[PDB]
Image (spheres, coloured by chain):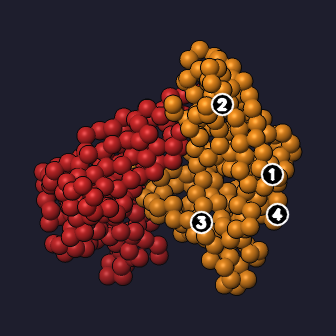
Chain colours: A red, B orange
Amino acid sequence: HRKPSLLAHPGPLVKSEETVILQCWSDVRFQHFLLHREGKFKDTLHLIGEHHDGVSKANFSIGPMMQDLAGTYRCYGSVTHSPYQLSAPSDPLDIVITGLYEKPSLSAQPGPTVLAGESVTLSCSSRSSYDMYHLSREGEAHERRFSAGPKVNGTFQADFPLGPATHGGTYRCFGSFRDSPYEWSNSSDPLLVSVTGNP
Amino acid sequence: HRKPSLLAHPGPLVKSEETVILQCWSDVRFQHFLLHREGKFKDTLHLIGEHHDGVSKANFSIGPMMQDLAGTYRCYGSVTHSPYQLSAPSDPLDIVITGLYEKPSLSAQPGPTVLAGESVTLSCSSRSSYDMYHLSREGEAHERRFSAGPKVNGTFQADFPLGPATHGGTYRCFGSFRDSPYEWSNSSDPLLVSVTGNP
């Protein structure tokens, strides 16, 4: 009696007003699903699942984004002859808000034009007391978080060792506080890491 | 006076007899390079760099692979009017041998056919006392290591949380001991992780 899947289109990071979709589905005939949200505004939803060949689905849309809506979501599914026998919970998915506070500074190192093979360490910071820092490589699968190294010259940074330079890329950085893990700051200005090639 | 780059074609993992190449280069006019190997058979090499437009280069070939040749390499470069004024050392690159001992067992979980969005945790093990475990996603950029969880039912495994299932893929697993970090066992039989898609 497996659990459903919880996706997020466009993606987990959402700017204010910006409204997002959380497609919960399974290859089963789940009659209807529940979308629970853990955290601040602990709330629950319900949707009768559509049934495009081989797959049931409930596309919940989290309306105009706000701080009270970002948090951990988990999805459930139940079938006709027992809609109160809930399925196993789907892997928790975090939906966050972006642009709440000042954007950080994202420096590269060695520099932003290393040659193929050279290891790179993107490292961002701020004068603000951010407790975390998130690295988003333009589109690339997912993000990477990191605990800040508080106070040094007023700044608080975190270094992200990307390892030897694979391909180029555009990375952005976000800062957040422990307080509310789903509330993030603006996006650091985009950094183009350019990997000079070899024969 | 930057350092050169050290690549490895085909790649860092080398089976016995199999002979590999370590292309060290820079966009500078390095007259000649040095290839030092740290570890077991501490040895050093020298090569006058060729000069294909915009780039000098020394392609050292580590002959018939054996345990005494695998280890940490670092590359240096010096220019004509001072070939004894060495450059900064290039990022250490590890060259390893594969197939020294029994291959491990690479199980998937939930299973090897999760749906898009579902998180996966490849987890391999062995009856042998491996202290480490390395995950190689067929071609995918690089590897990921992990400390084993010794003795449980005779076995010693390590779980690799791949996170939510991006794309499918073929993963292999290797086991090694602390003793010689460059000596690895055979490759676990290939695992095809198939990510069922969504609308």
Q: Say whether marks 3 and 2 touch (CB < 8 Å).
A: no
Judged from the image, the secondary structure of the residue bearing numbered disc 3 is loop
Earlier in the chain: of badge 4 and badge 3, it is: 4
Earlier in the chain: of badge 2 and badge 4, it is: 2
The residue where tag 3 is placed is: B146
Relative to residue B167, is residue B20 depicted above or below? Answer: above
Q: Residue type at mark 2: give it.
A: Tyr
Relative to residue B149, is residue A113 depicted above or below? Answer: above
How far apart are labels 2 and 1 at the CA level?
Answer: 24 Å
Q: Which circle, 2 or 4, is nearer the viewer?
A: 2
Q: Which chain does the numbered disc 2 sit on?
A: B
Residue drawn at 63 percent across, 16 percent down? B52
How far apart are labels 1 and 4 at the CA level?
Answer: 21 Å
Whether residue A87 is visible, yes or no, is yes
Q: Is residue A90 left or right of residue B142?
A: left
Q: Is residue A18 left or right of residue A133?
A: left
Answer yes or no: are tags 2 and 1 on the same subunit: yes
The residue where tag 4 is placed is: B101
Q: Residues within 10 Å of mark 1 (few under 14, many from 20)?
A: few
Q: Residue type at mark 3: give it.
A: Phe
The residue where tag 2 is placed is: B84
Of residues A115 and B82, the one drawn nearer to the viewer in this rendering: B82
The residue where tag 1 is placed is: B41
Answer yes or no: are tags 1 and 4 on the same subunit: yes
Judged from the image, the secondary structure of the residue bearing numbered disc 2 is loop
Answer yes or no: are tags 2 and 4 on the same subunit: yes
- The x, y position of residue B137, in whole percent, is 61, 52
Q: Residues within 10 Å of mark 2 (few under 14, many from 20)?
A: few
